Image: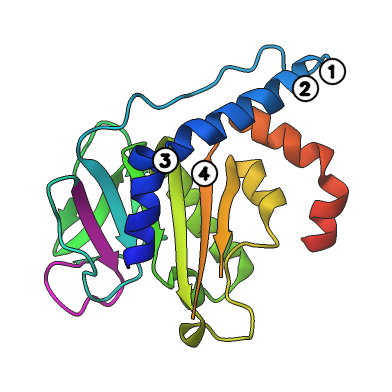
Amino acid sequence: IKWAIDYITKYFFTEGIYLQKRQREQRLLESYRAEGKLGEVQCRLMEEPPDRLHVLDVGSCFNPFSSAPHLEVTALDLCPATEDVLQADFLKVEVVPGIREPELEEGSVRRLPASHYECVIFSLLLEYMPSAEQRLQCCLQAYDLLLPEGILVLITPDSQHVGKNAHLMKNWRYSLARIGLLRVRFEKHISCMVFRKAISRELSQHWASIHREEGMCEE
């Protein structure tokens, strides 16, 4: 979808949002260090964004945006409609270092490269999950797939969710911060939510710890 490609462009290239949020996290880290906390935290920052970004789209049975000069797009789904969407169960794929391209067995993705993608897009993926645990498991997978400071983009039309609540992890910043993801954009025909792989998972954990009361209230 256009919104995600437009946000990706702003985040890495035209508005520098990756550096805005880097500053905000760095100023939060210093806040805690002036509190006597998080002294030994080491941060993981991305290099200058490459000229071709690596984008993984999960949950679309059609391939929405073809690969283009500055975008290498890999699309995956349990039930692909055509051949340019790879068949995979996102929850079963093993996310591993030491590779750079999907590893296929019998026409099915078995392994994906860890810490490789600038952006992971969930195209209704969470609406297919039978439980809140498995929705969190999708986010755990995305986290392992993302490069430092990469983004997980959730793009959900209002017509395509069930339950009057589009599953966007909006009430889940506590648990998502626990795994290293901080919310960086929410915009409302469609709902769009973006999480960022924070410069330090320990930093994000400590933010969750300070907001544990509100976190457990929302669950």
Left or right, residue 124 beside residue 191? left
The amino acid type of the residue labelled 4 equals Arg
Mark identifier at residue 32: 2
Q: CA distance from mark 3 to mark 1?
A: 32 Å
Of tags 3 and 2, the one toward the viewer is 3
**Whether residue 138 is situated above or below residue 44 in the rendered picture:** below
Residue receiving disc 1: 35
**Magenta part of the protein: which range?**
71-85
Mark 3 or 1, which is nearer the eye? 3
How far apart in space, not on screen, are marks 1 and 4 (Cα)? Answer: 25 Å
* Residue 118 magenta: no
| Whether label 1 touches label 4, CB < 8 Å | no
The residue that label 4 is drawn on is 196
Residue with the mark numbered 3: 15
Whether residues under marks 3 and 1 lie with C-beta atoms below 8 angstroms apart, the answer is no
Q: Secondary structure at mark 1?
A: loop
For image coordinates 33% across by 47% down, the residue present is: 9
